[PDB]
View 1 (cartoon, rainbow, N blue to C red):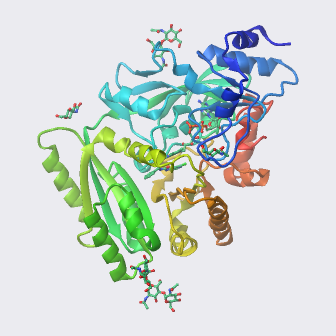
View 2: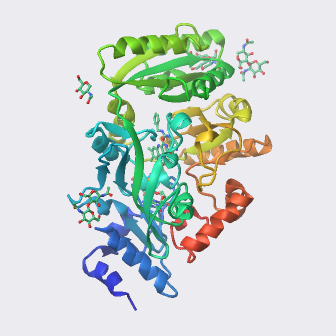
Length: 496
Ligand SMILES: *Cc1cc2c(cc1C)nc1c(=O)[nH]c(=O)nc-1n2C[C@H](O)[C@H](O)[C@H](O)COP(=O)(O)OP(=O)(O)OC[C@H]1O[C@@H](n2cnc3c(N)ncnc32)[C@H](O)[C@@H]1O
Ligand SMILES: *[C@@H]1O[C@H](CO)[C@@H](O[C@@H]2O[C@H](CO)[C@@H](O)[C@H](O)[C@H]2NC(C)=O)[C@H](O)[C@H]1NC(C)=O
Ligand SMILES: *[C@@H]1O[C@H](CO)[C@@H](O[C@@H]2O[C@H](CO)[C@@H](O)[C@H](O)[C@H]2NC(C)=O)[C@H](O)[C@H]1NC(C)=O
Ligand SMILES: *[C@@H]1O[C@H](CO)[C@@H](O[C@H]2O[C@H](CO)[C@@H](O)[C@H](O)[C@H]2NC(C)=O)[C@H](O)[C@H]1NC(C)=O
Ligand SMILES: O=C(NCc1ccccc1)Nc1ccnc(Cl)c1
Ligand SMILES: *[C@@H]1O[C@H](CO)[C@@H](O)[C@H](O)[C@H]1NC(C)=O
Ligand SMILES: *[C@@H]1O[C@H](CO)[C@@H](O)[C@H](O)[C@H]1NC(C)=O
């Protein structure tokens, strides 16, 4: 027997089973794994979400797991619902009204539907002279999707990840109950969902903190051949003083074998800059080159430009990058934030976007980053042609709420390490997948206590180690409270 509200979804054509629908919801950005769902739900309102979830909760024996597809940027099927129901979240935003993104009247925050993509949140915020303070490097991800992970970029060191910049949320638990939560109301759900990997319920609305939107960003890259100086400077730039003037701090690693190509692919360096850096590398006989990428946000004020030069000159004076290897660009704030979009378009038309992405994303404690550099950047990755950026930058644990579901290393400072390998060559995927296992194995043997990010584990012991025994028990307690039937986001392979 089908509940009335559930059948209604079928009648209205919102609950589809056609091969076209199931196929679209069976693959993701990873392009590595696939799983066809039994049906796809195209909700037009959050009421449709309650119907499905309420049905599953009241219907004994309900065999359909449910996933919430944001934009499917998951790497290993975390958004799939094998033989179940995949909710096409984007459908919640088809209606030209009511709006799915509303900047508060006081301009202190912006309400965004969970299905909304950050690029749109940005545009709707800029319209009101404000903007979220913590981003992701790529803006075509959903609010609910990044919040179910953490949401990190070069601003997280001072504003924390996106999950640390949410005032409250509307969540529909695995029981089918609509619940508004925050640090004051239903905090137990609020904390569980943030970094919760879609295990406790679906986020239909997230209240995102905003700050006055800067007009431009002074964009700089500093080059190093010495990892010690590179990491020391990234830490100096992101160390609590209150923080330094930098609005964003990230870093890149360039292996010597493909130095010129990767430097050119940054879209930042000119061929003249590339030549200088390649020469520098040879002079120092470096097998790896490092680049700090940082920005200084600022407004159109008449003195802004001059003030920026002085602030930047001052900050750079505290650093140790190779003399004369500071490279500057100055762009509109939005242009910087959406800087990766241009890369996607190019790669896609070139047929290099819709390919396997055996990406390795992890958090490495500061005390072992130098060891990671030696074993990975100067070790495992040496002797290979790298297509895709190798991103490395420090984060401050103080800006992360351990009470939430997201797991992080125990040290005060840890690095986000993102090796965005693209299986561009024919069937080069197997090598890359093996390489990532080798990197993780290297870390396990060196005793490096890392945390993976946006990655799913297929073994319970791994998820327990990921969260930590105590934090795991907490995760289970919340799972038993918000999704006892273990139906939500089975693709994470935590309870499925
Ligand atoms: C493809 C990609 C991803 C990416 C990135 C660049 C690219 C090209 N750059 C990132 C960055 O700089 N920083 C960062 O923190 N993440 C970055 N990502 C990774 C991205 O955060 C994850 O892919 C994330 O999953 C969000 O992507 P998306 O919005 O597309 O979500 P999904 O893949 O479809 O789903 C992820 C899991 O979350 C659950 N889910 C999704 N929406 C909801 C809601 N609204 N409520 C509760 N759960 C939700 C799914 O069920 C799934 O388990
Ligand atoms: C954005 O603000 C609008 C107010 O204009 C909200 O619209 C209301 O939404 C509820 C439920 O979603 C409806 O019952 C009302 O009829 C809507 N009123 C209007 C004016 O259309 C909308 O919910 C808000 N969305 C966000 C971002 O939370
Ligand atoms: C960095 O990689 C370059 C290759 O791009 C190495 O240079 C090559 O060295 C071999 C051995 O002498 C020559 O046969 C090639 O012609 C060189 N490539 C060119 C044309 O530049 C370089 O040795 C590597 N540096 C380090 C420290 O590993
Ligand atoms: C330039 O850098 C390379 C790589 O770091 C140095 O390493 C080479 O010499 C080492 C000493 O015998 C060998 O153990 C390495 O295998 C060899 N590099 C490889 C893998 O070919 C090299 O000594 C440096 N140049 C010098 C001598 O200053
Ligand atoms: O994709 C990222 N940057 C995309 C990018 C940045 C700069 C140049 C080119 C691509 N970063 C990132 C971080 C954490 N998790 C994931 Cl899955 C990805
Ligand atoms: C990977 O992408 C290609 C090209 O779109 C597609 O043909 C293939 O089915 C995808 N495989 C997976 C596992 O998604
Ligand atoms: C910054 O200046 C540019 C050009 O003068 C203008 O288009 C933009 O709207 C300004 N930013 C603000 C305050 O919106």
